[PDB]
Image (cartoon, rainbow, N blue to C red):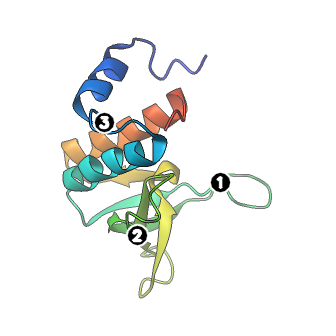
């Protein structure tokens, strides 16, 4: 198994603390989104560890992460708005938080981002 998480305590806690009011994946995406955006000490920065190359190799684009994307896009994945400080610098795009590594951010922001990544790797249940 992935073993990124291996004890059910975090699954019981998140169930009883973050998505108590939600019973379907669309609602639970909004539960995740709400607390995550409220926890992100945005704006911040990261590296977009983009795997989408033709060779499927990782590529690393330095980005300023403006905040979460519109909630309407985030019904399925925790998207974030990003500016290409590693390239274009003067324009903005959207990225999967799932495809980013946060840099030089506050501990509670880094932990929220890490916990999304760990959850997603442990299983995309919602």
Q: Check whether the beta carbons of the residues at disc 1 and disc 2 lie within 8 A of each other.
A: no
Question: Which residue appears farthest toward the right when viewing the image?
Answer: 55
Please tell me which residue lies in front, 30 or 41: 30
* Disc 1 crowd, CA 10 A, few/some/many (<14, 14-19, 20+): few
Find disc 1 in the rendering and name its residue.
51
| Residue 35 % position (x, y) | 24, 47
Indicate whether 93 appears above or below 26: below
Give left or right: position of 52 versus 93. right
Q: Check whether the beta carbons of the residues at disc 3 and disc 1 lie within 8 A of each other.
A: no
Find numbered disc 3 in the image and state the secondary structure of the residue it sits on: loop
Give left or right: position of 43 versus 4. left
Indicate whether 33 appears above or below 9: below
Gap in Å between the C-alphas at discs 1 and 2? 18 Å
Find numbered disc 1 in the image and state the secondary structure of the residue it sits on: loop
Indicate whether 118 appears above or below 97: above
Identity of the residue drawn at 51% across and 27% down: 122
Gap in Å between the C-alphas at discs 3 and 1? 30 Å
| Residue 79 % position (x, y) | 45, 59
Please tell me which residue lies in front, 75 or 24: 24
Which labelled disc corresponds to residue 81?
2
Q: How many marks?
A: 3
Residue 15 figure quarter: top left
Q: In front of the other: label 1 or label 2?
A: 2
* Disc 2 crowd, CA 10 A, few/some/many (<14, 14-19, 20+): some
Which labelled disc corresponds to residue 31?
none
Of the image marks 3 and 1, the number of the one nearer the N terminus: 3
Please tell me which residue lies in front, 91 or 6: 6
Find disc 3 in the rendering and name its residue.
19
């Amino acid at each position: 198994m992935a073993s990124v998480e291996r004890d059910e305590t975090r699954e019981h806690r998140i169930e009883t603390e973050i998505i108590v009011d939600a019973e379907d994946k669309e609602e639970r995406a909004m539960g995740w989104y709400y607390y995550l955006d409220d926890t992100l000490e945005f704006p911040f920065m990261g590296k977009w560890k983009k795997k989408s190359r033709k060779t499927s190799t990782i590529e690393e684009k330095t980005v300023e992460v403006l905040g979460m994307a519109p909630d309407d896009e985030c019904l399925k994945d925790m998207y974030v708005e990003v500016a290409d400080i590693g390239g274009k610098d003067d324009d903005v795009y959207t990225a999967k938080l799932s495809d980013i590594e946060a840099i030089d951010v506050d501990d509670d922001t880094q932990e929220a981002i890490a916990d999304w990544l760990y959850w997603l790797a442990r299983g995309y249940k919602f």
